[PDB]
Amino acid sequence: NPNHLSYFKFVGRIVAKAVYDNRLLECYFTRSFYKHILGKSVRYTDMESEDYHFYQGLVYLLENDVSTLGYDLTFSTEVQEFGVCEVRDLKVTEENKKEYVHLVCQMRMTGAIRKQLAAFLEGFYEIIPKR
């Protein structure tokens, strides 16, 4: 839909309108999306439901030595957004991976939805103050 961002801004407005009216919607958004509307980072355990084999990959990165991979990785990943696939930088080491799993989960959740998200957040904060 070429206007989809506008409809996501509409639904953010309608959610904030439901909150203003104090009326319950049958929305059941992910903890990731509720965190985005609250401005909280997601956590890697959220990936288990969204992309189990990518969660499993991050869990194989956690509590395992990088030497188990047998080839190197860096802070860059291939992401499909809007049907275009692009390799994007995220900013590997024993110190960096703690951030990689946080940041890689940020990229995987928001990258493909960042423009829908910015429209929804504009609709929400238009009616319900972020703070």
Image: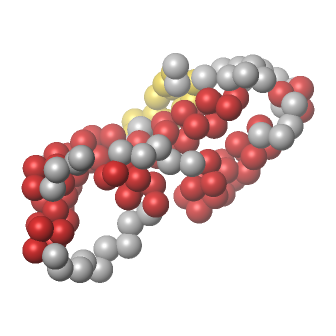
Q: Position of residue 60 (x, y in %)?
A: 80, 43
Which colour style is shown? secondary structure
Q: Is residue 5 left or right of residue 103?
A: left
Q: Is residue 73 left or right of residue 51?
A: right
The residue lying at 24 percent from left, 42 percent from top is: 118
Q: Position of residue 16 (x, y in %)?
A: 16, 62
The residue lying at 45 percent from left, 55 percent from top is: 32
Residue 50 vertical position relative to residue 54 in the rendered view, above or below? below
Q: How many marks?
A: 0
Is residue 51 among what the camera can see? no
Quadrant of res 68: top right
Quadrant of res 46: bottom right
Judged from this view, the residue extending furthest toward the front is: 131
The residue lying at 40 percent from left, 53 percent from top is: 35
Is residue 30 among what the camera can see? yes
Q: Nearer the viewer, residue 73 or 31?
A: 31
Q: Position of residue 63 (x, y in %)?
A: 83, 40
Q: Nearer the viewer, residue 37 or 10?
A: 37
Q: Position of residue 90 (x, y in %)?
A: 52, 24
Residue 34 vertical position relative to residue 39 in the rendered view, above or below? below
Q: Is residue 47 left or right of residue 24?
A: right
The residue lying at 41 percent from left, 38 percent from top is: 111
